Amino acid sequence: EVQLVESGGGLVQPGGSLRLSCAASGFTFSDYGIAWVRQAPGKGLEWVAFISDLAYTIYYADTVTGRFTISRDNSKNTLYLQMNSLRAEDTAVYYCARDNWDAMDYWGQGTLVTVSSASTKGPSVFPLAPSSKSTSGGTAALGCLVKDYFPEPVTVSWNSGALTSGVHTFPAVLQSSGLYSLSSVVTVPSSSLGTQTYICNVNHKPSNTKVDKKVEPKSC
Amino acid sequence: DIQMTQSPSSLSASVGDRVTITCRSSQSLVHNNANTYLHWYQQKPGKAPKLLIYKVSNRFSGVPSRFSGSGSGTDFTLTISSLQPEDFATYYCSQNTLVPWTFGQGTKVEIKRTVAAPSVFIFPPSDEQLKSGTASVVCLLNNFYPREAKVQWKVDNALQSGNSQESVTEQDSKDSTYSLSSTLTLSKADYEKHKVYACEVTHQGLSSPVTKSFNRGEC
Amino acid sequence: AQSQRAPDRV
């Protein structure tokens, strides 16, 4: 029931600014200190800022000091991190974590900040239809191609979350064009093909692209 | 300023094995209040870290009893008493006694598993992608172990080199396997001037390389 | 150097 929800992340030009927001819920917010911790893609955890209980003490990481400002509004149950003069070195999933007074015990799911001069692009969604040349069998595979978006992240589900078994959503690959592309694949019984619908639910929030793609067999 | 060094940075262990992860401080983590703020985190793929152990040895709410902590001053330890498939993750120690608060590098735990051959599927480009002018031919290697595999692309016996990308899934939390998609990307112009699209896969669980192929045409 | 490990309430 304890939750911290980060928002306000996104794409920013280098030198630009963002204000991250963390909406607290399910505890006494005014009782606890709140930390920010960031994780650059494929990298370790880096602590960045702390605001105490009533804001009396505030800590920054040297890497961040002067540019980032941590603040809170106890009456709003919200924490803020104002990030100025963003370098590429700041690209990271930024976590807000509540501190026990001994440990950061509850973290939010994170908001991704991408510092880049590239521009947002929505993806195209294409079906990966079951069986090539030879039809039928015992276990089939189908999927969706989510092609050519920037930046991360993209979300993929199947049948609005009702289908999870056999699902592999692959990490995105950065193509030579500076655009991302992934596949989400599912294995299902062959006998089920044509007696059930398979929809992939694609969301790319940064570009307001939200697409439901039906995937089925064809003629050849 | 406290440097947190973990040992090892990664490891493979079988299910049921005892696994020990070491954390080293450059400075005592005993606070002035006599407490020692060393904590351990588990981070699974694309999820936030979860608190496992706080203050050296305290198991956090809902943490299974096979996870424990140990140590004093400079040298600390995380033990997994009997490793389970869901225990795949990166583990981090952290200190809270001094500012800045610091983490170790992480120790990635992989689950060692019996060899499993991939299931190989090939997908021609949909007509709809074709209309946008591109062709992606996808090759899926499903539920295999170990992670290493080679995928070779051929178009009418012409070797394809550098025009294909691969993505591997993180180890599955239930059956401990990996999956891999290789995407061959062509112009639709090029795609339509050729017939046989073949994916050749090499893997330890495969006696002999397996080729999945199709013959072009919305036929 | 040492971090505050008690709330601003104290």
Image: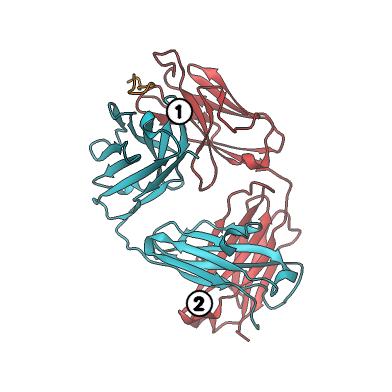
Chain colours: A cyan, B red, C orange
The amino acid on which the numbered mark 1 sits, given as a three-letter code, is Ala
> Which quadrant of the structure image shows residue B1?
top left
Percent across and percent down for residue A89 are 33, 45
User: Is A209 situated above or below A17?
Assistant: below
Percent across and percent down for residue B114 are 74, 46
Dot 1: chain letter: A
Q: Mark 1: which secondary structure? A: loop
At 49% from the left and 66% from the top, the residue drawn is A146
Label at residue B129: 2
Dot 2: chain letter: B
Q: Nearer the viewer, residue A23 or A101?
A: A23
Task: Report if residue A181 is visible in the image.
Answer: no
The amino acid on which the numbered mark 2 sits, given as a three-letter code, is Gln
At 40% from the left and 37% from the top, the residue drawn is A46
For disc 2, the neighbor class at 10 Å (few under 14, some 14 to 19, many from 20) is some
Label at residue B7: none
> Which quadrant of the structure image shows residue B113?
top right
Task: Report if residue A113 is visible in the image.
Answer: yes
Percent across and percent down for residue B32 are 39, 13
In the picture of the structure, the residue carrying the numbered disc 1 is: A103
Q: CA distance from mark 2 to mark 1?
A: 50 Å
Q: Nearer the viewer, residue B46 or A161?
A: A161
